Image (cartoon, grey):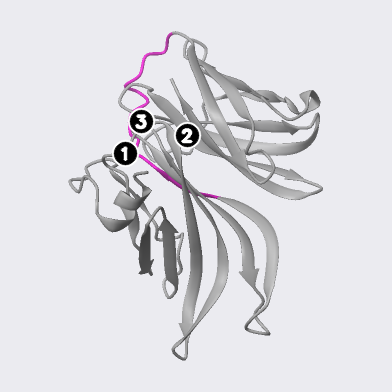
Amino acid sequence: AGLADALTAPLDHKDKGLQSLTLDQSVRKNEKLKLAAQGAEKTYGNGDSLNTGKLKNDKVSRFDFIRQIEVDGQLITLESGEFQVYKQSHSALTAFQTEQIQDSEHSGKMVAKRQFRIGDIAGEHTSFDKLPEGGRATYRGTAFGSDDAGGKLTYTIDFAAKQGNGKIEHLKSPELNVDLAAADIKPDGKRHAVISGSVLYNQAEKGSYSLGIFGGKAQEVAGSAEVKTVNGIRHIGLAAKQ
């Protein structure tokens, strides 16, 4: 696995769009980060990166990590989990999966939560008035979230009518396949466009999603959803290509 390559050496170092991902919110400005997999280990802090140049497209990479600090020269393993790293065409994103973590009173206890969060959505886009207003664009993607990380969605956008739509499918049970609330183009992007709509949960509840278009000609789509429930909020990541 190229996991070991990307911890021991850099990848394509030219970077003029995306050949890497930024970690300046993945770690605190004071704290220590250790990552490891498949015979290698990355040791950093404050605000670094992870390199993705000469890896495959349209796939997920798997990693072990911990976020920690040194106290009076002593090392405590504060929170540990899964570093879930998506590589696509023109775009890439991270997600967090914190589970096994220390209690900050006894310096040697453990606690087991199951806390997922979305990460940074990499790939600059600056050009919707550069696309045609014609056709229908088919899309299909992975859904990855705090209860959702076994299913996958179907997505579309009528370029001729400027309206997005979708559906969530491939679930453990059939009532869990939900309709997606059809949504038009709305203002948010600093020099680009967005589709932002609503998300129906187990035929109940009230979630929310936002995503954008990527590449030089609508090659893929990426962004985020948050479904809020009586169980609290599930963040779901988007990964879908033409």
Q: Could you say whether the residue bearing mark 3 is in a helix, strand or loop?
A: loop
| Residue drawn at (50%, 20%) of the image | 139
Question: What amino acid does circle 3 point to?
Answer: Ser
**Of label 3 and label 2, which has the lower sequence position?**
3
Q: Which residue is drawn at 46% across and 69% down?
A: 28
Residue receiving disc 1: 55
Q: Nearer the viewer, residue 139 or 74?
A: 74
Q: How far apart are marks 3 and 2 (CA)?
A: 11 Å
Query: Does dot 2 land on a helix, a strand or a loop?
Result: strand
98 vs 227, left or right, is: left
- Magenta: predominant secondary structure element? loop
Write down the residue under mark 2: 222
- Is residue 113 shown above or below 234? below
Stretch of the chain drawn in magenta: 118-134
Do the residues under discs 3 and 2 have CB atoms within 8 angstroms? no
Could you say where residue 98 lies in the image, as x and y percent from the top left? 60, 59
Determine which residue is flagged by label 3.
89
Disc nearest the viewer among 1 and 2: 1
Image quarter of the N terminus? top left
Which residue is painted at 50% across and 73% down in the image? Answer: 68
Amino acid under disc 2:
Ala
Give the spatial CA distance, label 1 vs label 2.
Answer: 19 Å
Q: Which residue lies furthest to the bottom in this view?
A: 72
Q: Is residue 125 magenta?
A: yes
User: Alpha-carbon neighbours of circle 3 within 10 Å: few (<14), some, or many (≥20)?
Assistant: some
Q: What residue type is labelled 1?
A: Leu
- Nearest the eye: 129 or 215: 215
- Image quadrant holding the C terminus, namely top left
Mark 3 or mark 2, whichever is nearer to me: 3
